[PDB]
Amino acid sequence: KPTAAHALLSRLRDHGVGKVFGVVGREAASILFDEVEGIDFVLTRHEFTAGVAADVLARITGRPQACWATLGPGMTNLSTGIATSVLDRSPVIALAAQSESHDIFPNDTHQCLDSVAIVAPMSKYAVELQRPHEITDLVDSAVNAAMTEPVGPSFISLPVDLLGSSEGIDNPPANTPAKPVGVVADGWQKAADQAAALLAEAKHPVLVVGAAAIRSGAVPAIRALAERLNIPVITTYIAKGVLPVGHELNYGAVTGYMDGILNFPALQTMFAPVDLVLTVGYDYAEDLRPSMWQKGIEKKTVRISPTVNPIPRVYRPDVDVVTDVLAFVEHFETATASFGAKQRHDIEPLRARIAEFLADPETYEDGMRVHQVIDSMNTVMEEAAEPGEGTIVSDIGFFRHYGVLFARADQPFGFLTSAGCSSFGYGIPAAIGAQMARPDQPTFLIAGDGGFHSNSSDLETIARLNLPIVTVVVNNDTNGLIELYQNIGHHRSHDPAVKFGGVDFVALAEANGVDATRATNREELLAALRKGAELGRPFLIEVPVNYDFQPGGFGALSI
Amino acid sequence: KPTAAHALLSRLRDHGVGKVFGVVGREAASILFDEVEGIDFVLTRHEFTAGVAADVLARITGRPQACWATLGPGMTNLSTGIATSVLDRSPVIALAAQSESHDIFPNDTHQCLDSVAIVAPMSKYAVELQRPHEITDLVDSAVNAAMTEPVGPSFISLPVDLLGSSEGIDNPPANTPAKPVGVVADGWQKAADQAAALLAEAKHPVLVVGAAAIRSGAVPAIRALAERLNIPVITTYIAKGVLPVGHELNYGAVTGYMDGILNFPALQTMFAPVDLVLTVGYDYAEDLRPSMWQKGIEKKTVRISPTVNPIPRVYRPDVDVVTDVLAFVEHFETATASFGAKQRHDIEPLRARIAEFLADPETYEDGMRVHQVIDSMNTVMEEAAEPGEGTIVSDIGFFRHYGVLFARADQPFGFLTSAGCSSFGYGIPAAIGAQMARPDQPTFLIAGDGGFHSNSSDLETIARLNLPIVTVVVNNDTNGLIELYQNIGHHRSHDPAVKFGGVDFVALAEANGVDATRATNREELLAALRKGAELGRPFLIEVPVNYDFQPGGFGALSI
Amino acid sequence: KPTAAHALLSRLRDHGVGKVFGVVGREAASILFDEVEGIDFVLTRHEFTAGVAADVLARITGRPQACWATLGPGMTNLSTGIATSVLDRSPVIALAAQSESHDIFPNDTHQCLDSVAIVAPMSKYAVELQRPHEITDLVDSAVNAAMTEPVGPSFISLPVDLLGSSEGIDTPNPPANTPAKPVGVVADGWQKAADQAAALLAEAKHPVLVVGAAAIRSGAVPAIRALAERLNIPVITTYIAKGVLPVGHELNYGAVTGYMDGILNFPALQTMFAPVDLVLTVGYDYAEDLRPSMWQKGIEKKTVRISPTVNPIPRVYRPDVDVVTDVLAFVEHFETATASFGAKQRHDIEPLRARIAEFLADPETYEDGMRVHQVIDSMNTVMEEAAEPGEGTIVSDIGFFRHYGVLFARADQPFGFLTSAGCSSFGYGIPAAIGAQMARPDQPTFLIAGDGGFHSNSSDLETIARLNLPIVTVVVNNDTNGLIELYQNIGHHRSHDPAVKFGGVDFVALAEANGVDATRATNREELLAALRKGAELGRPFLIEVPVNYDFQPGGFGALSI
Ligand SMILES: Cc1ncc(C[n+]2csc(CCOP(=O)(O)OP(=O)(O)O)c2C)c(N)n1
Ligand SMILES: Cc1ncc(C[n+]2csc(CCOP(=O)(O)OP(=O)(O)O)c2C)c(N)n1
Ligand SMILES: Cc1ncc(C[n+]2csc(CCOP(=O)(O)OP(=O)(O)O)c2C)c(N)n1
Ligand SMILES: [Mg+2]
Ligand SMILES: [Mg+2]
Ligand SMILES: [Mg+2]
């Protein structure tokens, strides 16, 4: 007789789920993961990897995805993946086993924690299964909550006895939302008209585009609007690629680190003459903060979001348009149909400074510089990928902000990083998710030694799934970002809190069954990248780097 | 001017803390970790390692210890270490950064999670700093709650702005408890006297000793009582070693897996003729459950614990003595002073079976058997360690229960594993904690491939701290324990949920700067261990193993 | 077949419970309250009254008591009684119905709230029943947590379907094993700490014992009295610890209230504490609102904290010596440690005693009603006449008048003066008097309440009449939340009537509408006559007294935190 395990997997399948990422515990006595045709288990080395892979697969597909952990520490390990989903915004169904229903005594029963209480504050929905047959409605409610803006994870705790029970089990339509449900304020049309009047008066407007605009399906619409009215497009970290590489209105992504990295007044060049900022699909969690565009002259602001403003302390837009992003753009197109195109502000000196970093021909004594590494990756990505295809993934660290500034993105989600949660070790699972979402496209990963090693064991998973991911590890034997913060705050370093000894990442990758090589200059790196891209197997490249940063140029980070 | 960062580290030092284990994030701008002489930061590759190292150091020293993480994902990563502490019972002060106080918007501000809400359900105490100068009293309250039975972790969330602030900062005695504050019921002496009357009438009593008895400082007292009255001593996993190896009253440790592993009615032999079970320092979390001693004739039970019984559904003792364990033993000595010694029951067939496993001279066609691996470790541990010294640490898996049955423990906490939480990956941080707590004693670690690789990156930490831990990795390319559960529940395996590809742990260890070798039989293993023990540096030994388990023998796991 | 309703009531009876106070809702379909011999339902007009009555019965008996409410708003109404129990410290089992288990959707199902989530922050224990037969073990765990210091309420949520189910219920219960008195925590080396306390006492010229309710719960009253009498150490109390020494005892130095200097226009705190060099806070609890700032007067002092709990407030109270142990255990050890010690010379508080006696004896006739001290003096006189020695209870509701009660009310036994020190909800008076009278069935029970607090919960006058409890109630009426008008003036130096002022309520007529005989009294002579009539009536009685305060907002600096 089919049990709740079968009913659970069946309902996931009904919602389009074909993979469950995770680590299985003793609940394997209740669930094999062969119960339902068309749904396969994906075993990782750590639960964090499972949660993040599901998050990234969910982002790219735009469909709910699923991850799995055992009770107690299984669930707490998964919780960092849950945190990624809640802050980065992805519809994930997170599932964890629990002690037998009659034996649930949190902090007393072996391996028993109060899972729902722990996960509730970091999720859209959290529940414990109580009556086996109800799992079908619990999955539906989890999906419902996961697919409402801000999209996020829903959690179901599964007592082992109930998971293996057929009591009451003997499906209605799933009706999975094709795109996220959102909120809409009465009179948003009048607000959008107010925004249009502001646009009429503005000499130098900009569109600041966040990921929610991509979820709404508004990329083509935003592009046509921008092109018609000659409005520059600036993006958050993961909204890179909403305009093609080389497009005249592609003014790039912003990071608070950019002035410090470029030794150039980048933020002032970008924003100083701007008089109207339209934050299209705005989300504070993406870390493009109002302080970043508040440069030079005073600006009017328009917020467009399928959510009520959660942060009026920080952002009080002149016009708040609470509605679906695509709905807004379509109404805005009509309202601005007869408007003359604007003159856009000059950012050529910034474009020149960026092109200079990328072309940097210098050979340094102490390893490569990260801008040279990314320039090399861009070159090979452009060669390996079809037009409008390919993914560059970045883990977290100082180098990540080089990825934000310099990495090629020729499609929405063509550059992937964690903007909301920013857990180190993000790189491997995100590359797994990306490669699975785009099986015939090249997937490159860049990670630093600190973050990469925090989660490097899942190299084995990459080898086992034979995902042809090309990974570049930039190694300076340091949590480099953190050494920068030490210097910002104290004007000196303290090595015991930031410094490592040597890790041979080439030998590490090969130990996991991943072919690898060391590259120490542009010539060796291009060769290694070209080899990896054509290998038909995963490949890893270790690059020695150094940063030589100055803490004085990073005032934009202050909160 | 000294800030809350200084006040925090100073108060930790006041409470005897000399090390802070963790990973530092952007809060480094507010805290360097050189503010206070006598406290050193111990940088790990993952926050879980930091939390568990502190837990184990706190267990062995009996003093509060400290761990550290950044905001958001740092805190969620640390929470698996916090869960270890809460279920395994150790006084850990867990510290995590938080977003700037005026910018705390959980699930909206970049990396901002509601840390206190997430950690409260799995801690003794959880608070967020609000006024910088109060950090001193918050540390004190954290220590107070951590050092009350059941001992556990206390959590302080630290907004980056407040941590770096000197506002209101211009010490009172710390008065750190020497041993845990315990719960004591009125009339416990009367209950203890009722226990004495039960002992007088009993023909075959046993002492079942848990870790709380060790925390109480009751080991010598319990030994003296057991010897005078000829009462056999049986232990939980980590209470192994309360009697020396070879002691006539050392009846061994219990695990629910023992019948299936030994292919022998082990629980029956241990408990069948027993008529009185005294659970001295009982804790359900340790997973020695009433169903395990409920074999053969009817038994009376006496519970002794410095806590009120949290599980009356499961355990209703005939006599419940709520008091300090040492206080009970001292009162019990007086009440039983004139008692004649008992005739102890015969467990020689069980001792014989255990000895048979250890001496197994066969070289199997596939890998070694885990009992052979442990016998080899025992041999070299006995050679390398002074009498009453040495630590064998076990990670989590099927092999762990072989450790419980077979591993040598010649002192309290001589065999260390995670009995309450049992997170895989526990091995490395526990060995770090153990070696640091016992700097002049040998520390051996056994871990399986599944659990070891979940947290294997902290091999670099072992190399960096130059801790001379000898690690044995028992590799069957499987989450073996989980395949067992598949077979128990379904009478077949499902490889996608349990099977890995090959990892070369020798090459992996060497990539991290740890010398390593492979050993495939007793001779190679003994040679490798003897080399490791004398090396004066960390060493790793990979051993191929197989289980060939029989699912039908594990009925004790269900009840 | 017996259901979980029967099992629940049987387990409560096993733990010695004979009454369940509350208001029943639709869960009556699952529970009648006649299922079990020896346990009766006590119906109130509002759930707050039920929780507080259980709280007070638990305080005086020292044993766990029980209250009941329906789902949703039943539970939220009960929660103010739960808050009373958690802050005032009493072992109460709070029970509330919940939606059918399969229909629990908080904030969506009709009347469905997340009860466990709401009550958990203000309770020792909070759980929802899931498998009917487990109610027995849930009650045991609830009692266990309620009876561990600091004592407080434990809450069980009862889905109506499961409450009415016989699934898995086979009717002999295991032993109840209720703690004999509250369980506490004990620090290793508390004896050494106690010896350090004795060393401080050896050197002290003018030590004092500051005694809180936890000392009473520990059964330490006779032991503390014997210690104080031998060593000539004055005893000072919190509000409900009045009566640990008899009225007139030379070492009975009275209770402390932060309001005392301003009510008396006297340096009362200075007189009480200035020459003291050692303060032993015996069974200390911050919630009782005797704060360190109140004894920190005059010369520098050493402090000893004795409590069956670890210090929860080191920011506020850092004792020189902290003795974490059972209060009785401490006193017995301290007796041995100080056996050789002779008696101290106690400090002189006669000027304060004279001021207090002056208020009580106030012979003035005022144009604008009586004064509260005159009202309390009259109550004291009649209480003394009506009660056997060492007996009687004066109950006080909450308001400005309550602190007159603290200073002036007779207490000739522990809990002889009863008020809410931790929670201090207005309306407390009636349920407390109900609980007190039931706990002490043959003793006089008087209640003083102000018009604001009394009318907040006056409907349970009908309950007093129905239960025929011979409580004598005095309502002191000034048509104002007077305490709040005081705070307006403290903070702003003026009043604002819309926030504090009422129109006229005839409490005599109100009482009679509820079936309680009543009368108005406007001077000492009429009040003494009314009280004497009430005390001998054999029925409840209510007396309305017009009062005014004429307070001085400038004299309440001690209140500042
Ligand atoms: C779970 C978690 N803990 C701590 C941090 C703080 N942190 C962010 S990135 C990072 C890694 C920095 O080192 P690396 O990956 O080598 O990149 P680098 O800054 O040196 O360029 C750390 C420790 C984090 N981001 N996530
Ligand atoms: C954090 C966490 N996730 C999942 C589990 C389930 N689990 C327990 S031990 C273990 C490892 C079993 O494999 P291995 O370490 O190789 O030991 P083996 O059973 O093969 O002897 C796993 C996956 C766990 N214990 N902890
Ligand atoms: C539940 C609750 N709400 C508000 C208060 C604030 N408060 C305390 S006592 C009280 C009553 C004051 O008026 P009254 O009972 O007439 O006594 P008075 O101060 O006039 O002497 C009020 C409103 C309270 N104590 N309890
Ligand atoms: Mg680095
Ligand atoms: Mg294995
Ligand atoms: Mg009034």
Image (cartoon, coloured by chain):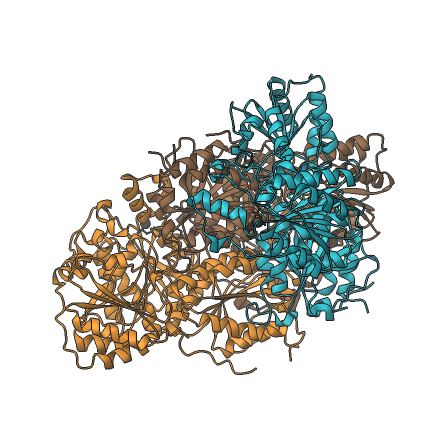
Chain colours: A orange, B brown, C cyan
Give x and y (percent) for residue A248: 16, 71
Task: Tell me the quarter of the image containing the C terminus of chain B.
Answer: bottom right
Q: Farthest residue to the right: give it.
A: B201
Give x and y (percent) for residue B537: 45, 38
Residue A521 in the image: above or below residue B376? below
Q: Nearer the viewer, residue A401 or B408?
A: A401
Question: Image quarter for residue C196?
Answer: top right
Number of numbered discs visible in the structure rendering: 0
Residue A254 in the image: above or below residue B44? below
Q: Is residue C492 visible?
A: yes
Left/right placement of residue A74 relative to residue C243 reads: left
Residue in the picture at 71% in, 28% down: C249
Question: Image quarter for residue A536?
Answer: bottom left
Task: Tell me the quarter of the image containing the N terminus of chain B.
Answer: top left
Give x and y (percent) for residue B431: 52, 42
Question: Image quarter for residue A245?
Answer: bottom left
Residue C559 in the image: above or below residue C39? above
Q: Nearer the viewer, residue C205 or A320?
A: C205
Q: Nearer the viewer, residue C40 or A288?
A: C40
Left/right placement of residue B268 relative to residue C120 reads: right
Residue in the picture at 79% in, 59% down: C40
Residue in the picture at 21% in, 68% down: A206
Q: Is residue C211 visible?
A: no
Q: Nearer the viewer, residue A466 or C281?
A: C281
Left/right placement of residue A339 relative to residue C358 reads: left
Give x and y (percent) for residue B405: 67, 48
